[PDB]
Length: 173
Ligand SMILES: Nc1nc2c(ncn2[C@@H]2O[C@H](COP(=O)(O)OP(=O)(O)O)[C@@H](O)[C@H]2O)c(=O)[nH]1
Ligand SMILES: [Mg+2]
Image 1: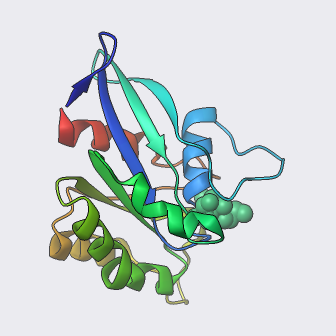
Image 2: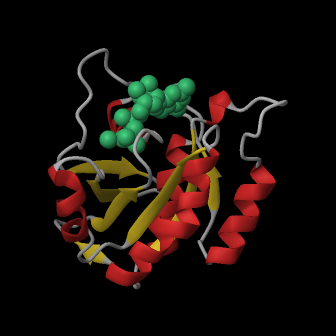
């Protein structure tokens, strides 16, 4: 619950296994596309203005990673976070299981006061006949972990991107 110029402001941190699509989520959400160019391991934190209810919110968006120096820097990203997106890829069951084994506990340790939103990324990839994570599985995990919501999204297909960040704003304001 911050106010930075005259605009309500929110800090959102994005966490989850490598390659679940965290950097693409932020690029697609804020830039409206994923550029054909070298995608960085971690996007430096930045502010994005989002027009929502009928007002403007300033979102302070923090990408994170677990490779190279970013693994060591990650804990420092959490301070004063209002919302944490717990991200996995729906076609990667390992990443889903790690929400419970690694990511939710890490968040509870460093920033228990943050609200969490469970985010099922790469939903464009879900298909019958594999062991892809279902919407019911995401809903159940959200329930067990006390997240505010489970939201499915695709950066590539532009599905659910605004919903993720609109729900983030909603649970704070
Ligand atoms: N099909 C599909 N692929 C995606 C999507 N988002 C990301 N990817 C792919 O997943 C790879 C890893 O994404 P990235 O954002 O770098 O993952 P990060 O390590 O969690 O930040 C990228 O090379 C994309 O090719 C998506 O919504 N749909
Ligand atoms: Mg990344």
